[PDB]
Amino acid sequence: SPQPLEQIKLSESQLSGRVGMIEMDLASGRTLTAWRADERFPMMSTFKVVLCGAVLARVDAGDEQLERKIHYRQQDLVDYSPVSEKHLADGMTVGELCAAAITMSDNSAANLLLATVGGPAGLTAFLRQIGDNVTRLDHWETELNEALPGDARDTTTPASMAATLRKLLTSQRLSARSQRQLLQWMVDDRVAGPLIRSVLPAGWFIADKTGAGERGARGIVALLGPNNKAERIVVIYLRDTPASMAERNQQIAGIGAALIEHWQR
Image (cartoon, rainbow, N blue to C red; front, side, top):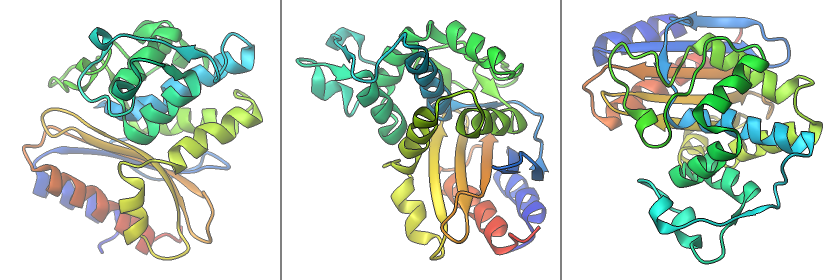
């Protein structure tokens, strides 16, 4: 592979789209590699990690329980509800909903959860409360994936998303149990995790959440590292490309490969 920057440049050129990236030390927060780190990209399903961060903060405060059962109706369901559609009769626990949202990208699950944190506005308020003054949610699923050109709604920046993921995962903000739970849900991703794990060299930790939207919008937030250890946060977003899903996937993979091959910093 080319050097990480060379590769990212190549991906923009080949995709005719905009790429945003940050690679960050998890322990210290040190920014190692960056590209358009301050430019805005649609979060898409990557927001479900921050969502469940907010849910866990409520659990920590005693205003919520992961065991609480939520009951809903079929009329409440939105496009793509692989787990939630199976539980119209019995319902789902808050914890099960976070599992479905993060591990299966279940969209109705995400909406049921978003309600409990005060909706898009409530989640945005949460972000500002932990010192993210950039990331904002404005829509529910599935409108949050529209990726309208120039639209600031429903967006993050690579730098802000990496900072916020670090804040949720390693700072005093969530309880130890909540920090471990948010990570495990990412470890347990069924959508892209097993695929990624299958092509990573032996010895590499991966945990992740992916997203996809309109106009070529694609992304991943990931924890990655050698010697079986979650060493770095990696955030990669693409927007405004006409390319196939396969090629968008391949380009993000190539960027990952460049990072892994040229890891020592």
